[PDB]
Amino acid sequence: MKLFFKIKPLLKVTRQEEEMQAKDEELQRTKERQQKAEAELKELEQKHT
Amino acid sequence: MKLFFKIKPLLKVTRQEEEMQAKDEELQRTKERQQKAEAELKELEQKHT
Image 1 (cartoon, rainbow over the protein chains, first blue to last red):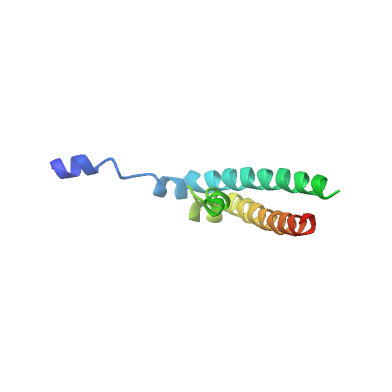
Image 2 (cartoon, rainbow over the protein chains, first blue to last red; image 1 turned 120 degrees about the horizontal axis):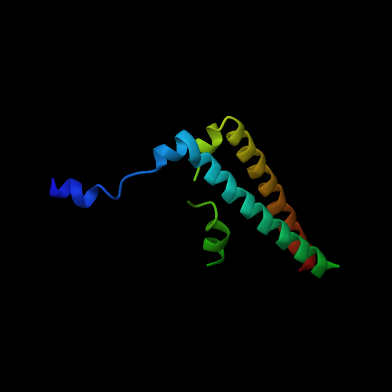
């Protein structure tokens, strides 16, 4: 029982995300990445010009 | 370190997102867009060089 105890925390979240939530989080991350990429691209284009 | 950098984002993120049916679709679209952006950026960088 002590074991379960120290261990009980490392557990989750992944399941919950899948049920939801996980997809939403992933989407958000992707969006952020895309935005960053776009910004970088714009900068690169300017530099190239 | 650059590697970790481009990569640091993909981390968390999914399966749930993909499933979401609407969410999943959105995620897929976002991913595609991101990929395209990345390709464009790479091309731009090469041109700049």
